[PDB]
Length: 608
Ligand SMILES: [Ca+2]
Ligand SMILES: [Ca+2]
Image: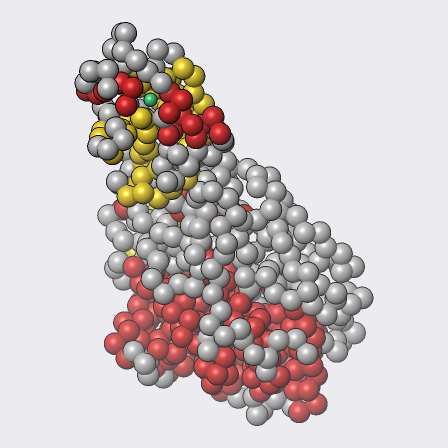
């Protein structure tokens, strides 16, 4: 059988790679650093934190809130299994990472920021998370009473209520904070009944289904968190506003639970809360359609057994429905025959994602996993190209990709933003599915698993050429191809070492040597007079300081800065470049000159 504990371990770790903001020191990788620390600065608020949505760096709160709710749902249903796997703490930390962010986005009762970053502006740049905020502004978008967003506020209410539910025993004060914000956001959504102000997510996370399903979703979670029947009643109030399967009176059943349709999960929760036939029949009708069929109709299946609802995020849909199948099949009121059908269906969808069709569709897991997920920071280009490097510098452990077509066909290409898309909501229900599969079938996680990668290219270094000319003239490029993690540097300098024995032995003062910047792409570039390095051997160096100029792996030729400079003695003084340490290195290998060491804020970071 497949190792569900390892899969669960990695599916949860995936969210660490999506973290935005000032990162905790207990992350388990060496290739994510601080990012987007100025989020919210355009409106005078701290709106850092949360997750980047997909392979981009926009923070879309509707799918982010959906994700957090689903992860908390996994905790709620499968806490003990998650504890045993060793991953419950990390999952809870990720849930709180998102929820802390939602709370900051809600500075007053009827004002909610639902997006940080602009989709069109953000997606123009194929650069790592640690550099994206240098390339374009990241505006903060909000809804309020004059420009409302019932769908996203209700969605966030559900996330904070679900967070309160799972934290109320271990952190009563935080749960009380979450539940208050939840009820306020619910009232906000219910008061406005409109998405008129929810515009910044157009073409990315538009709500075609509206907010009535979200109101039942949020109401049910609020009730579960603190037992307020006022919100269960409101949740049931809006059931008759849910989508209806056309040509029938049935609650819609032929799609699936996802970020833009939560009435499937809402029906399941309301079923367990009230045991009412309406909800039990609705969810059974849905799960039947996905398994054995309903009234002569059944979801499409690939020849190799994948339930194939659509071509967009097909594995996201199959694994999420499987999760719901797990929850309902574990319920005592679920008819036994179909409890077995449902859980058998859930395992097969889990096993398809993990490799039953011949390859894994989970990055970094199993047999022949995808290697080119459509993900900027895991690829980690230093020059704003999907094609450079031609392989990902990092392994996005645990990422469930979009998946194959209805014939099980699939191509692993970074440019296929459909088959190789990855996203927060793709892994959300997946985590809960793997929790149940671990609870039932086991599979040992990797002990103390850490995503500490080997650095496969030199991050920061000088490339240089030189020519002798009554002294020396240097043409240098100071590179920042950092990757572990990518980072912006603005305090970089390097040293050029010389042996001035022939010069000082002839009676000349090193301070009369001319040092000059000829040209530099760094406007702050400066060069020091010779500095004594070894009084016994008359070794000196000149410091070329580019502090003040950003050098980072991004676009606009920012991953390198050219500096041309000259070091020339007074006319007539002896000069021998051939005994100069840095000159010798340049002529040995100008590509990477260890003999011109690089310093960041005065600390050596490369070279001898
Ligand atoms: Ca909706
Ligand atoms: Ca010399």
